[PDB]
Amino acid sequence: SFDEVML
Amino acid sequence: SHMEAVQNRIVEAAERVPGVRGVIHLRARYVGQDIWADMIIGVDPENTVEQAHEISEAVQAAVCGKIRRIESLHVSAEARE
Amino acid sequence: SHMEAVQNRIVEAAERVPGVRGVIHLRARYVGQDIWADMIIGVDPENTVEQAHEISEAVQAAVCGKIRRIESLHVSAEARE
Amino acid sequence: SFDEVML
Image (cartoon, helix red, strand yellow):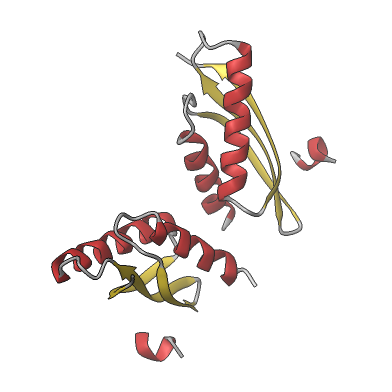
């Protein structure tokens, strides 16, 4: 996901 | 790392948009050869919420316009000065 | 190929310099992770040779300023229109 | 060289 990408 | 060069371009593109008082925060990541990024810009505390939204959308268009590998960019605004 | 993206940036940077009437020619190559490029710009045939030299130098500075991987850039000018 | 680079 986007939030998951942001790590 | 070639990510630093991309981050510089994002910051410099955002900073040329009227009403941007600096980039408060920027996180960028690669998803394959695309960039996904999340940014916070500073704005005049006395701007309206609607104006801050407009400046945000302007940054989104400008940054995406200049840096073609960006496929997702979220911009939010916070008061600065 | 990521060279196309760099070539677009060079062309667009040159074209924003006052007195540039298009990029006539551009050849770019990698030397390691640096770019070496040779460009011909169009200018007003009625400009002086000295003015064309000034516009060339302006392009060189602008393009190198925007595209940090460029380590050698030659710019020459030819009449256009 | 530069001219040689230009291929």
